[PDB]
Image (tube, coloured by chain):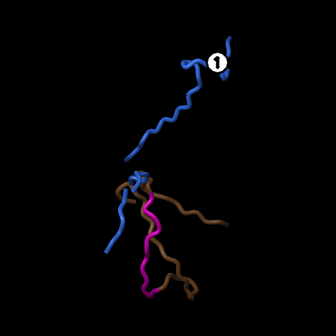
Chain colours: A brown, B blue
Amino acid sequence: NIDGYFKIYSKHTPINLVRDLPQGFSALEPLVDLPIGINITRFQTLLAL
Amino acid sequence: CYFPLQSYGFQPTNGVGYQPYRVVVLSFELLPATVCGPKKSTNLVK
């Protein structure tokens, strides 16, 4: 979240393990640099039960 | 106790002063400039 932008870079890939995050390389392209320009200190996630 | 608002009640025979007048107020706000003018751009040759 910079320059008055919110900065989201991302990627979509699979995994084939059981309980971990993997090794192996990749890169994240951008998603959006959002024109919000606010102050943020923390957050929470959202997930559907 | 009187109603707050009145009706103009425009008629076709309205006078230049009373005739109805559409209004549009355009205020520009900047703080990424998103809306710009007719980007006039030119023709690409090589």
- What amino acid does circle 1 point to? Pro
- In the visual, does A44 lie left or right of A4? right
Residue sitting at 47 percent across and 68 percent down?
A: A31
Position of residue B36 measured from the top left corner of the image (x, y, whole percent)? 40, 52
The secondary structure type at the circle numbered 1 is loop
Q: Residue furthest top?
A: B1
Q: How many marks?
A: 1
Look at the image and tell me in which quarter the N terminus of chain B lies: top right
**Magenta region:** A23-34
Residue sitting at 55 percent across and 85 percent down?
A: A15
- In the visual, does B5 lie left or right of A19? right
Residue A26 on the magenta segment: yes
Mark 1 sits on what residue? B4
Image position of B1 with respect to B21: above or below: above
Image position of A10 with respect to B26: above or below: below
- In the visual, does A12 lie left or right of B6? left
Position of residue B9 measured from the top left corner of the image (x, y, whole percent)? 67, 21
Look at the image and tell me in which quarter the C terminus of chain B lies: bottom left
Chain letter for the residue marked with disc 1 in the picture: B
Position of residue A20 measured from the top left corner of the image (x, y, whole percent)? 52, 82
Image position of B24 with respect to B8: above or below: below
